[PDB]
Amino acid sequence: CMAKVVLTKADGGRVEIGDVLEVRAEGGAVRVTTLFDEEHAFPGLAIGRVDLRSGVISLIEE
Amino acid sequence: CMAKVVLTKADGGRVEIGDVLEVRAEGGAVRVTTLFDEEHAFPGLAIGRVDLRSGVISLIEE
């Protein structure tokens, strides 16, 4: 399975991160690990939706 | 891609749901839709982890 994470900021800015390996919600943040051995951490967010057709994982405010 | 949902109860009991299409966290619950037009609601849970290698989506107590 190939997945991307999407989120929208309070200002309407949208961020998408591809080549996702793992998404974990812990300690008040969402951590996104990718295939390039990088992690992106988003404090105050939760995992809102996982859509297996599209491969999209949507983040939301916790 | 195949995904399954997994959750562990307070007593150590595990539940697994296969053939998952969509997982959504809203209104204090997680809703799991499957490929056979079945939907399962889990109140009090959140989406804790999404693991793209294994295809496992883990639910946790909110």
Image (cartoon, coloured by chain):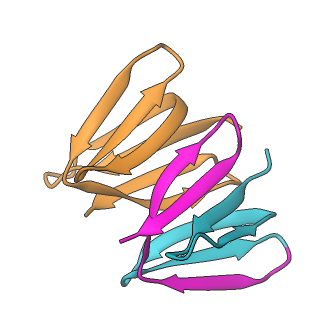
Chain colours: A orange, B cyan
Extreme-left residue of the structure: A11
Q: Is residue B49 above or below residue B11?
A: above
Tell me the quadrant of the picture where the N terminus of chain A can be found.
top right
Counting from the top left corner in percent of width and height, residue A29 is at 25, 48
Counting from the top left corner in percent of width and height, residue B32 is at 63, 74
Residue A18 or B31: which is nearer the viewer?
Answer: B31
Residue B51 part of the magenta-drawn span = yes
Tell me the quadrant of the picture where the C terminus of chain A can be found.
bottom left
- The span shown in magenta is B36-62
Residue found at x 36% / y 25%: A39
Quarter of the image holding residue B61?
bottom left
Counting from the top left corner in percent of width and height, residue B52 is at 63, 38
Task: Please give left or right for residue A52 compared with residue B9 in the image.
Answer: right
Task: Please give left or right for residue B21 compared with residue B11 in the image.
Answer: right
Task: Please give left or right for residue B16 compared with residue B61 in the image.
Answer: right
Residue B2 or A7: which is nearer the viewer?
Answer: B2
- Secondary structure mainly formed by the magenta segment: strand
Residue found at x 41% / y 82%: B44
Counting from the top left corner in percent of width and height, residue B15 is at 69, 71
* Total numbered labels: 0
